[PDB]
Image (cartoon, helix red, strand yellow):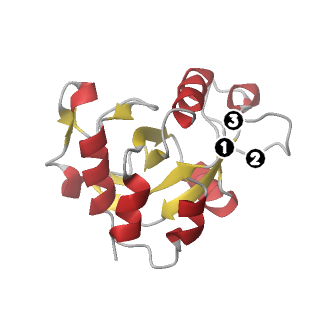
Amino acid sequence: GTSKLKYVLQDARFFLIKSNNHENVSLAKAKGVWSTLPVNEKKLNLAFRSARSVILIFSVRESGKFQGFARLSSESHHGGSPIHWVLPAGMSAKMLGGVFKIDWICRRELPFTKSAHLTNPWNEHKPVKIGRDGQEIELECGTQLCLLFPPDESIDLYQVIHKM
């Protein structure tokens, strides 16, 4: 069903994540972590304290798809085991030093062709697929986008709900 999913998304904030490569999204799905550049890291940390749920919606550049979405379960932290991110050109490991823990809500993909009817008021009403890494997605557009994903029957949102 979708009722627990809607409860998790109630009054959530949504952020678009643009990964330059598939490897890092696969690592994130296996390990339940994400790292981003400092400008977005600060924004996510602020958002985490402000809303019952902060949702990251992942898209790998050039893939034409979203690869899933996840909920922040922590603010960023430094000093753990260095995550073996594949680093884009010009990006240093220190730039991804802050690690967020995430709980995946859906690990299925969604093609951009299926979200063409959704525009983001916080990015000039451009289709929600369009946006820089870290672009915030307005509540209604983000909720509807998440509800477009195929159900991920492997995930039990009961544990997620208890962290809210």
Residue 76 image offset from top left, x and y in percent:
69, 35
Contact? badges 3 and 1 (CB < 8 Å): yes
Q: Residues within 10 Å of mark 3 (few under 14, many from 20)?
A: many
Comparing marks 3 and 2, which lies closer to the viewer? Answer: 3
Residue 109 appears in the rendering? no
Q: Are marks 3 and 2 in contact (CB under 8 Å)?
A: no
**Could you tell me which secondary element the residue under label 3 belongs to?**
loop
* Marked residue nearer the N-terminal end (3 or 2): 3
Q: Residue at x 37, y 73 (%)?
A: 151
Q: Amino acid at mark 1?
A: Ser
Badge 1 is on which residue? 74
Residue toward you, 152 or 6:
6
Q: Which residue is mark 3?
A: 76
Dot 2 corresponds to which residue?
Answer: 84
Asked if 130 appears above or below 117 in the picture, the reply is above
Point out which mark residue 161 bears.
none
- Residue depicted at x 34% and y 32%: 131
Sequence-first disc among 1 and 2:
1
Type of the residue with mark 3: Ser
Q: Position of residue 145 (x, y in %)?
A: 28, 52
The residue sitting at 20% across, 24% down in the picture is: 124
